[PDB]
Image (cartoon, rainbow, N blue to C red):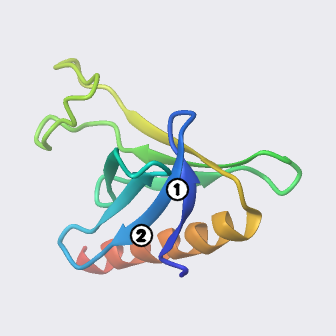
Amino acid sequence: PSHSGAAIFEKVSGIIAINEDVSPAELTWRSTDGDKVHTVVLSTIDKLQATPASSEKMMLRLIGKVDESKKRKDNEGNEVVPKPQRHMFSFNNRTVMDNIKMTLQQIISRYKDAD
């Protein structure tokens, strides 16, 4: 279960799954309740940031590039004004965050192959 692991998003915890069967791939997030499901685009991730090993708080932040006038906006608080969107996640498990972090990094490398 390296591609899928529990992760928090917006003070809410749920299971995070990595969907690569599509194109571009996407990271799915299902709440613990299973009533709310969030999907993230891995193609719009210029990079992947994570908390240091010296921080008891496990959180992985993803940079949603800067310019996205051509890319469809999430519509969830995004305005016409071009601005960089970042998604900060909170992990309740070091091993779980490490399983996703390393897995998410692989996807990046895959995007580089394209160009």
Looking at the rendered structure, the secondary structure element under dot 2 is helix
Residue 42 against residue 55 in the figure, above or below? below
Residue drawn at (14%, 34%) of the image: 69
Res. 11 image quadrant: top right
Image coords of residue 29 (percent x, y): 40, 54
Dot 1 and dot 2 residues touching (CB under 8 Å): yes
Question: Which x, y percent locates residue 41?
Answer: 29, 55
62 or 10, which is in the foreground?
10
Count residues near mark 2 (Cα–Cα under 10 Å), then give few for <14, some for 14-19, many for 20+.
some
Q: Amino acid at mark 1?
A: Leu
Dividing the image into 4 quarters, which one contains the C terminus? bottom left
Residue located farthest toward the right when viewing the structure as drawn: 54
Q: Quadrant of residue 80?
A: top left
Q: Which mark is residue 48?
A: 1
Which residue is more in the foreground, 48 or 59? 59
Number of other residues with Cα within 10 Å of mark 1, as a class: few under 14, some 14 to 19, many 20 or more: some
| Amino acid residing under circle 2 | Ile
The front one of 109 and 21 is 21
Residue under label 2, please give it: 108
User: In the figure, is residue 31 to the left or right of 56?
Assistant: left
Is the N terminus in the top left, top right, bottom left or bottom right quadrant?
A: bottom right
Q: Residue at x 57, y 61 (%)?
A: 6
Please tell me which residue lies in front, 46 or 77.
Answer: 77
- Percent across and percent down for residue 112 are 34, 73
Q: On the picture, is 27 further left or further right than 61?
A: left
Which label was assigned to residue 86?
Answer: none
Per the image, label 1 sits on a secondary structure element best described as strand
Residue 44: x and y, percent? 30, 52
Which residue shows up at 39% across the image and 70% down it? 18
